[PDB]
Length: 264
Length: 213
Ligand SMILES: [K+]
Image (cartoon, rainbow over all chains, first blue to last red; front, top):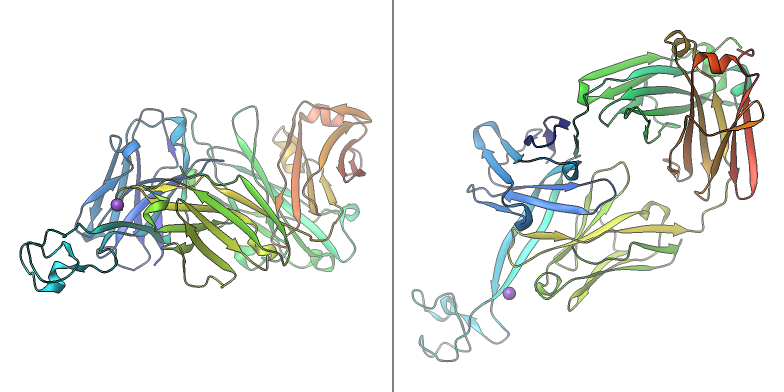
């Protein structure tokens, strides 16, 4: 399964944060779909889930703000969180989960059903099958079973009153003084965007060895910037074209910047 | 929240244990799971039902539980195991899940390595947009601690500096970046600018100048 989160990257304080989870093909009608989030530097936090039958379960601490809905016909599950605050800024993941309460009997006991008791007492635990009204009957042990089976990639959602801004992309060109013998560094500077995040590839993914995209810095203006760098053979600088592909999904922007070596 | 140590470390080849302490209503209910979060990747399930391994998880990752404390044990530590690890459990209902506070695992013993430093002057395109950023990229160092200082001519510059916290590259060494934002006039008003990187008591400095390119 491959789960996909979609929705706005930016939410104003007190407005409602909404997301949708879709697949790349697999059906979600027979699976339980849940939402997990992680704020920067904080722990994973469970939000809630909805099972195949449409029953929902929420994190107690957030039950009053959350709503999860299923749309079998669109193969979609949605999430809504009312009253957004900066504490709700986070990466939001949709998941498929294993969720069930397993009943078992203590050692040496047997379920009423396995004793022939198919009506009253079929779900109780008996030390033997002598009497449906056995006074030594006991209730089953409940094991609440939870785990995440599949994880989406996550969608970062920022809560802020500042406005979206797409990035300006500038080349970090290699120069005669800046090589390292057989290899040369070249890059792209991705300036002044909001909110996060930006991702960067090189030559549309055909160049992956040597690539590093740095974390963003937050400037005094409230706008982020980052850089991406790749190491390539110095001999290829006059002949091979190098392009950085910058993706800024919060503004629906993609930029392909050709990075030309300097004459210097 | 379940209680984990904020950090653990071990050396290559050795074994480390990450504990997850809860109560009789979550961990003590007996179905704990573990998750691995590598910076850049999506979370990955490692362990479910206390001891069962998810598909693809080598045998050197093992889960266990004793009462209200569960433990993830990683043997034969490899560099690729550095990550954040989280435990989890239902609490009183299968729909009420709780996660642990997270544990950052550091794998020790890789070779020391001095930083490579590349300093880019403002691009011609940025200057024509009436802006100027110097970009200092610091790569392929270990261990992951550096200091970065900027100079205009030979005097310190603090205004307009931003620096990222080092993080691992795909080859398991560290990299970091630093920035000096100037106006085009400030850029042109000095003879040179420098970025100096201190690593393990030694310093690499790169210089650029408005008149050189
Ligand atoms: K119980």
